[PDB]
Image (cartoon, each protein chain N blue to C red):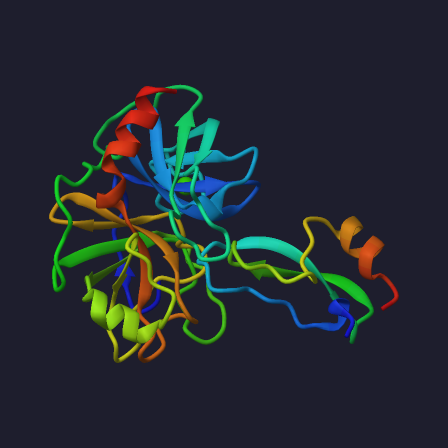
Length: 223
Length: 57
Ligand SMILES: [Ca+2]
């Protein structure tokens, strides 16, 4: 996260880290057994780390639970990035508590201008590389489909939305993928892609979770 | 054009996945951050794969 702030330990209790010997993506806990992340975060051997703040230290509230299933959307397109969503089943159920909690799925899509909270352990620099120890947070608005398509001609599908600030300075970045965009207590987005980080005229692009609610509920229930 | 001589490509996705690329200036396979999509070919999952494919380029 570029241009954000330190969340505070366990203030975003649905945020998880996906670990494959190191942190490579985020995710969002949606029940004690299931996490939502991005399809491009698929790897075998994922370990989900819950209750994290400092991801480089063992601080006392962590739960480390292996993925038992990592289910990419069946229509994920790795060239257009359409349907960039994945469901991860935990091999055992997480113990839910004040620092490890689920986030609700949307009941309807969010509108342009709705303010959301984006979080993760991704790079904090727009030029260069600095990866934080602790979780970072950013408040940013959903942008109009028209502005999104203007920023990225030919690239934005009905399952993507843009969020951020056109002036630059505030964005998700490498290592934030898969993580949450939460608006009024609902998971409306998944960190997906962009063009650079925090550049002028280049807002972040996010998977539009509201389009997948029926699929998410049925896939979870079928596995 | 030898793909082993191309600079490493992070791409537009926002993961932080460690991959290898052949660095012809140094003569060695080196690590870089891959964002998770739209990989180019100078992008390997291990040093061994990179050395096999690009070593000596
Ligand atoms: Ca920790």
